[PDB]
Image (cartoon, coloured by chain):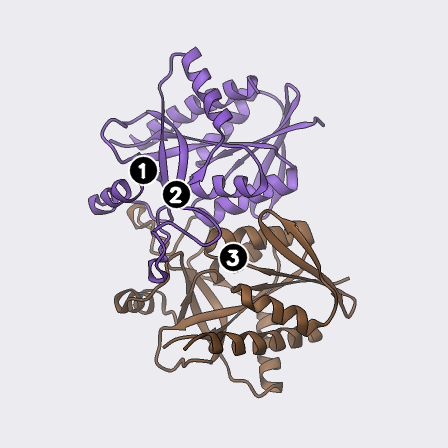
Chain colours: A brown, B purple
Amino acid sequence: VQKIGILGAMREQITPILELFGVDFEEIPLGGNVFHKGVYHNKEIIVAYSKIGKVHSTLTTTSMILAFGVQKVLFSGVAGSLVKDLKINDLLVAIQLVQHDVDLSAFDHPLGFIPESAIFIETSESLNALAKEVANEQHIVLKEGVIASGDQFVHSKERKEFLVSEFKASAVEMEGASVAFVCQKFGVPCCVLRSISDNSFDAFLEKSAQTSAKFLKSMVDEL
Amino acid sequence: HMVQKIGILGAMREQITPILELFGVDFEEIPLGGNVFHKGVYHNKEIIVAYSKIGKVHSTLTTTSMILAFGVQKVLFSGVAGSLVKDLKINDLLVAIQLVQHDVDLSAFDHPLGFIPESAIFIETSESLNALAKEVANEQHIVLKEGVIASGDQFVHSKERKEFLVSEFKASAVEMEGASVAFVCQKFGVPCCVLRSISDNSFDAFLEKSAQTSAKFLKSMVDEL
């Protein structure tokens, strides 16, 4: 059978996903997290909220793989734009992700680099081409970019500009890079999608929750 | 096979062969998620040893695999740290009573620095493993200090950052993996003890030295478990 992981970066994204898929979902607790497991079109679907920041999101993804056997992972959520051409409500597919807060510069490593790893983590060529396929069939503009992730909420103009000079990043958030890393380590194809959320707010989040559930279901139908 | 199983993590790859050697039994190598796990039997326990790799995502991943894939019920975590206070000097051994993620910053939503929703600023380790470390250090006339340990994904070297960690968190030392391991163990219900040799206040001689010291200490703890 197929086994597919869907991770949401905000708790409010989860209900809209379960309801769109239509099938019953068993609630299953493991290590502080909650995993929703259902059958749709004869595939196992595992859905969960990541929780906040890199340790939380690493734990959730690691448990999704080792405990539920998911074979592919789809991670939606929200990011802040760092460049003018990226406007509120654009959908961005991450080709590369960087942990922006990593600094081993004292040992002569460049910023973002950990030994036995790399500065930029790649996502799955096949899932990304399918997202472009889904987006075209649905008349959505899907833009391509580098996402930066870290355990700070980045608001200041100075930190934003450093992220663009050093990593060539388009957008910023808190979980993406850790999730894509874990998937690489286990040889599990991953796709990370973000709707742009800044350049009064619940409405933006609600709607973006509804439309991401639709886009993910459409990727699953093709898988 | 045995009923009891214990995980032993090292924050430096240099710490592993001394540990494997001192326990003296045969270890089988099991690769998983980019990590290598050494599985052996000593006394009436299965022992699982692994290097954590560097920083918070690495170490969170290794611990989760150790708990989930090999069923460890207790975890002992050794490595090196930097001093933040004057009475903590090179070659001291320190037990972390509590741990904090010093780099977390959600102050834009009015959260105290270090706090993440659904968690706490301070993560706790095992009172009973810590009192055991203390009993062992008495028996062998070894110095074991007790303190708060700060972790984050930057090698901290400036005076401004060191003084923020003291004033904000009352930390006594700083390193890059402790808080994340104590956090995961907490999430699964697994008692955890974190032990650090102080590396500051040549580097390699200090390392080969401390790896021997800490492997003896770790084995002294298991012989009493």
Q: Secondary structure at mark 1?
A: loop
Q: Residue at x 42, y 21 (%)?
A: B213
Say few, some or many: other residues with alpha carbon within 10 Å of mark 3 (under 14 / 14 to 19 / 20 or more).
many
Q: Amino acid at mark 1?
A: Ala
x and y percent of residue B104 in the render? Answer: 37, 52
Q: Check whether the beta carbons of the residues at disc 1 and disc 3 lie within 8 A of each other.
A: no
Q: Is residue B140 above or below residue A88?
A: above
x and y percent of residue A65 in the render? Answer: 64, 53
Pointers 1 and 3 within a single chain: no
Q: Secondary structure at mark 2?
A: strand
Q: Chain of mark 3?
A: A
The reply to whether residue A223 is visible in this rendering is: no
Residue in the foreground of this view, choosing between B182 and A183: B182
Quarter holding the N terminus of chain B is: top right
- Residue B107, labelled with which disc? none
Q: Is residue A158 left or right of residue B30?
A: left
Q: CA distance from mark 3 to mark 2?
A: 18 Å
Pointers 1 and 2 within a single chain: yes
x and y percent of residue A122 in the render? Answer: 51, 64
Q: Chain of mark 2?
A: B
Q: Check whether the beta carbons of the residues at disc 1 and disc 2 lie within 8 A of each other.
A: yes
Q: Amino acid at mark 3?
A: Lys
Q: Residue at x 57, y 49 (%)?
A: A32
Quarter holding the C terminus of chain B is: top right
Q: Residue at x 20, y 43 (%)?
A: B159
Q: CA distance from mark 1 to mark 2?
A: 8 Å
Q: CA distance from mark 1 to mark 3?
A: 26 Å
Q: Is residue B149 above or below residue B221?
A: below
Q: Secondary structure at mark 3?
A: loop
Residue in the foreground of this view, choosing between A177 and B139: B139
Question: Which residue matches tag 2?
Answer: B100
Question: Which residue matches tag 3?
Answer: A51
